Structures are given as C-alpha cells and as structure tokens.
Length: 49
Length: 285
Length: 49
Ligand SMILES: C=CC1=C(C)/C(=C/c2[nH]c(/C=C3N=C(/C=C4\NC(=O)C(C)=C4C=C)C(C)=C\3CCC(=O)O)c(CCC(=O)O)c2C)NC1=O
Ligand SMILES: *[C@@H]1O[C@H](CO)[C@@H](O[C@@H]2O[C@H](CO)[C@@H](O)[C@H](O)[C@H]2NC(C)=O)[C@H](O)[C@H]1NC(C)=O
Ligand SMILES: *[C@@H]1O[C@H](CO)[C@@H](O[C@@H]2O[C@H](CO)[C@@H](O)[C@H](O)[C@H]2NC(C)=O)[C@H](O)[C@H]1NC(C)=O
Ligand SMILES: *[C@@H]1O[C@H](CO)[C@@H](O)[C@H](O)[C@H]1NC(C)=O
Ligand SMILES: *[C@@H]1O[C@H](CO)[C@@H](O)[C@H](O)[C@H]1NC(C)=O
Ligand SMILES: *[C@@H]1O[C@H](CO)[C@@H](O)[C@H](O)[C@H]1NC(C)=O
Ligand SMILES: *[C@@H]1O[C@H](CO)[C@@H](O)[C@H](O)[C@H]1NC(C)=O
Ligand SMILES: *[C@@H]1O[C@H](CO)[C@@H](O)[C@H](O)[C@H]1NC(C)=O
Ligand SMILES: *[C@@H]1O[C@H](CO)[C@@H](O)[C@H](O)[C@H]1NC(C)=O
Image 1 (cartoon, rainbow over the protein chains, first blue to last red):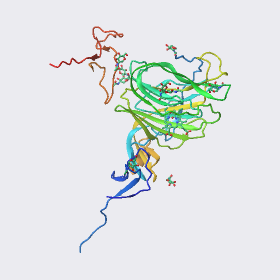
Image 2 (cartoon, helix red, strand yellow; image 1 turned 135 degrees about the horizontal axis):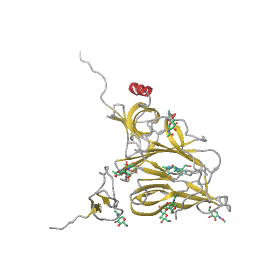
Image 3 (tube, protein in one colour; image 1 turned 45 degrees about the vertical axis):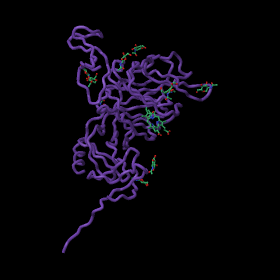
C-alpha cells in the first residue's frame, strides 16, 4: 500500500490500528516514533466500450 | 514484628452501585470512530460493589476477600492510605503469594512464599517538632523464602502527608489472572466527590502483564496507619486511620459494545445482556 | 525433581512449589509421612548408563 503521514495519536502501548474489517490502517514506525496511515493503492472502476 | 490491632468498631458491610464503571481496553490495537463488540471479563454495569471506608471520627476495614475470576478495585483518596495488595490462596507460607506495595519510595512486586500477618499494614508517624511525615512501620510479612519473582520500581517520593478536606484522587484497577499472567489495568482520575463512586465513564489502560504463575483465590488490601502524639497507647491501640475509601467488585464473562471516538478513546459502552434494551442496542450496533 | 502427586491438575503456565504432604487416603496426614501420606516431590534418577 501507500504510506502517508497521520494525525492519529497512538497510546504508548499500541503499535497497529485497524478498520472494522480488521485490516491494518495505521502503524507506528518502529525507528522514528511516528504514525503512518496505510492505504490500498488500487482504486477506481474501469469499463471497456 | 507484626502486631494485631484491637481498637475497632464492627459495622455491617456497605454496598454501592457502580454506574457504567470498570471498562478497560481489551487489546492493544488502535481503533477510532467505531462500535466494537468484544467478549471479556468485565464488571457488569449498574452492579453492587462492596464498600470499605477507613475513617477515625475508629472504623477501618481490610478483610480477606475472594478473587472470583478477577477484581475491580476503586479507591477514593486524599492522603495516600491504600498502598497495595496481597494475593494468594492461603496466605500462610504453605503456598506462593503475590505482594504489590508502594512503601512511599518504591513500588515492589514480589511473588514469593510469604508468612503473612493476620493484620498486615504500613505505618506513618506524625512529628510535632517539624511539620513532616515519614513512613516508619512495615508489618506486612514475617518471613519470605523461595522467592520467585521480584520487581522494584525506580526510587521516588510521594506526598504521604495527611490532607484535610475532600477526596481528590480516584484510582481504579482491574486485576485478572489468566494463563499464568497477572494482568493489571489502571486509571487515575482527579475528582471532588465526598462519599460514593463518581458517576461517569473512564476506560482503564493496560499497565502490567506479570508472569507469576500463581493460583489466586483470595486477596487483601494493605492500608496505612497514622501514628501521632494525639494517639496514646501501645502499637496495637496508639494509632489513627486517615480518611479513605475503596470499593470491590467482581468481573464476569460479559459481551460489551465499546464506542471508540475519533481520537481512539473508549468514551462509552453498553453492557450487553444487562437488560433487553441493551440487547437491542447490541443487535443494532 | 518432579511432582508426582497433586490434588488437581495445574492450570496452564502455573507453578506449584509447595511441599505439603499429599493425603492419598482418607485420614489426614498432619504434616508427617506414613501410609497413604506421600511426599509430593520425587527425584529423577539420572545415570549415564
Ligand atoms: C500500588 C502499586 C502502584 C501502582 C500499580 C502504580 C501505578 C502508577 N502510579 C502513577 C502515578 C502516581 N501514583 C501515586 C500513588 C499511588 N497510585 C496508586 O494506585 C496507589 C495505590 C498509590 C499509593 C498510595 C502518586 C502520588 C502518583 C503521582 C501523581 C502526581 O503527579 O501527583 C504512575 C505514573 C508514573 C509516571 O508518571 O511515569 C503509575 C504507572 N503506583 C503504585 O504505587
Ligand atoms: C521500600 O522497598 C524497597 C525494596 O525493599 C527498599 O529499597 C531497598 O532497601 C534496602 C535496604 O535499605 C536496600 O538494600 C536495597 O538496595 C533497596 N532496593 C532498591 C532501592 O531498589 C526501600 O528502602 C523501601 N523504602 C521504605 C521507605 O521503606
Ligand atoms: C487453587 O486454590 C484453591 C483453594 O486452595 C483450590 O480449591 C480448593 O481445592 C481443594 C481440593 O481438595 C478443596 O478442598 C477446596 O474446597 C477448594 N477451595 C476452593 C475455594 O475452590 C484449587 O484446587 C486450586 N487450583 C489449582 C489448579 O491448584
Ligand atoms: C536508531 O534508534 C533510535 C531510537 O532509540 C531512533 O531514534 C533512530 O531513528 C534509529 N536510527 C535510524 C537511522 O532510524
Ligand atoms: C494476634 O497476634 C498473634 C501473633 O502476633 C497471632 O498468632 C494471632 O493470629 C493474632 N490474632 C488476631 C485475631 O489477629
Ligand atoms: C446488591 O444490589 C442491591 C441494589 O439493587 C443492594 O440492595 C444489595 O445490598 C446488594 N447485595 C448485597 C449482598 O448487599
Ligand atoms: C524533622 O522530620 C524528620 C522526619 O519527618 C525527623 O526525623 C526529624 O527528627 C525532624 N527534625 C527534628 C529536629 O526533630
Ligand atoms: C523451599 O524452602 C525450603 C526451606 O528453605 C527448601 O528446603 C526448599 O528447597 C525450597 N524449595 C524451592 C523450590 O525453592
Ligand atoms: C482529540 O484531540 C484533539 C487535539 O488535537 C482535540 O482538539 C479534540 O478535542 C479531541 N477530541 C475529543 C472528542 O476529545
């Protein structure tokens, strides 16, 4: 996926964040203590005429 | 060095209603703006909890209580009277026992074969020469052998002076013993309420995950005694109790619907199968 | 050493170091060995042969 900057504020005991579908949205980068949002990089319908 | 305490006035045990209290974060996964349904050991909502209040006016209580699949322990304080717990089965050195204590300098967590005293307590002494308190007495256990787990926190000092007025600190704990792990969830809130448990919501955060491997069925709270020139007699009577209170409830396996707000905080919850309306709220999510 | 007698099975990741006398029979043992009163721990006999 695509990793972007995040406004989420993780509690110190948290490492991952999840949707209601249990797929990982946000992750705390273990090197630099910042939160990165993960987005699927495939998106959008396509039709052939 | 342990001594029993004789100057007591017996009272029937008081009971209080816990109003949507004792919720903790079930896992360590961030969730925001979601209605998450979980099943875990929770204190049921609107539940009757036993109330033990230590006051002088002398009425103070530290009995050995059951540990039924986990304990919710709230404490309203203004002068740091409740300062730890004892967990075990027999509490008489035949079996291993767990001791969590804040002795005003360190937090000590020891799993160890303690020979516990019938009235275990700590003791602070008032000085008339200078307006200062120091902790003097540590009468928890007589002997300690075969001493498995030990943790000592970094040194500190806390305000053990006896405050006068209203209760200020509410410290909430959830203890559970699952698969050899003693899990503690904690939460401290500032309050200004006088008698009962505050009405509101506050989610307890994970603190520890101690690998003690201990059978636990009973537990006992450790309190602190003021001793002053105003209290005459020997060590068994020459003492007074600062004003504090604690509340004990028992966890049950329950399904809860937790609401995580946009900042990732559990702001509200529904105890499922409390009443049929709560079941409807569960089904509708 | 290993524990040979216990009143009930251990819970997972539970440790029992108690050395109380096991009452296999009906009469209490009162902290002394004898008939139907066993020391719970027994030592492995490990020989190279
Ligand atoms: C009993 C074991 C015990 C536990 C589990 C505990 C947890 C605990 N208490 C804290 C604050 C604190 N805890 C206390 C005192 C207490 N808080 C309590 O739950 C109890 C029982 C006392 C003792 C009476 C005080 C005075 C502070 C600092 C509050 C302040 O900033 O004024 C902190 C935050 C420390 C930090 O800032 O990094 C933790 C983790 N403290 C303990 O002593
Ligand atoms: C509170 O408990 C801790 C641990 O028992 C005490 O700290 C130890 O004290 C002994 C004797 O002075 C020392 O040998 C240890 O090195 C200390 N261990 C530490 C600081 O980690 C402490 O003294 C106690 N404090 C009070 C007021 O009772
Ligand atoms: C954990 O501790 C409890 C209390 O010691 C044990 O339950 C007791 O087991 C004996 C067996 O004879 C009974 O006589 C008691 O009546 C029981 N008391 C209670 C409160 O249950 C329990 O067996 C221990 N569990 C493990 C795995 O060791
Ligand atoms: C090395 O570890 C520290 C954390 O202790 C961290 O600040 C630092 O970013 C790490 N080095 C690199 C190149 O990330
Ligand atoms: C009183 O103290 C003695 C030893 O200090 C102890 O054996 C006994 O159990 C105590 N009795 C009570 C009621 O606390
Ligand atoms: C249980 O809750 C009720 C309040 O509905 C209370 O009257 C009762 O005292 C509590 N249980 C006990 C044993 O006191
Ligand atoms: C001052 O207070 C400390 C402990 O609070 C005490 O040990 C000391 O004796 C006091 N100073 C005098 C002169 O009494
Ligand atoms: C328990 O304590 C007794 C007496 O000190 C000792 O004989 C025994 O070896 C100890 N067992 C363990 C596991 O420490
Ligand atoms: C979430 O955090 C922000 C701080 O940037 C704060 O302004 C906001 O009030 C918080 N939201 C809630 C519901 O408390």
